[PDB]
Image (cartoon, rainbow over all chains, first blue to last red; front, top):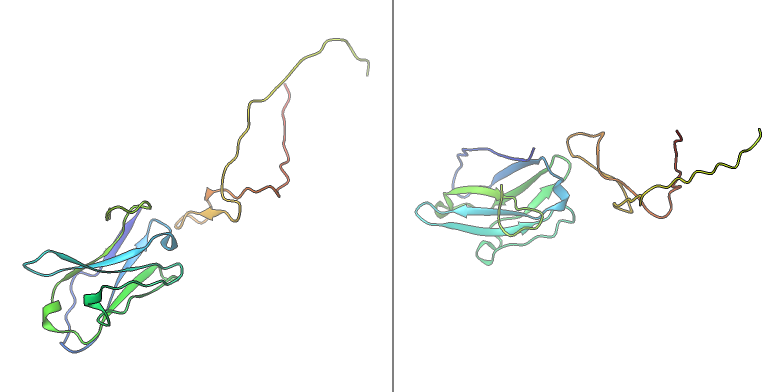
Length: 108
Length: 52
């Protein structure tokens, strides 16, 4: 059964670097692209990027360019994002995105 | 063995097979069950018929 675990709360200091991760199971991890998203509080969601565990081909947003380093690992079945030199305007909520194998929209 | 002139036809329907020709993909959790079996031209497709 498919699931995406995520740690709910994370407290940090501005100007430092934090390692956010989410866990993948129920499917085969190398057969799907993964996306990450940001909902600014008092605003809609913002899509940041696109990452594949199979090869490691990355994709960023230009407004997040050099801000997040999308990298993953295939042994423990998880993907990472890692915001560098964090400021106050990125105090927000975050999810990691799973679509169907077709991949129109984010199912789980 | 003496033979009699009583002949009986038999016949199977179209047996099929479909999958990945490179490697079998297993379920991620259950590491004993297959998802798509591995089938190419190169396998010995040995049959095992049964008779009444």
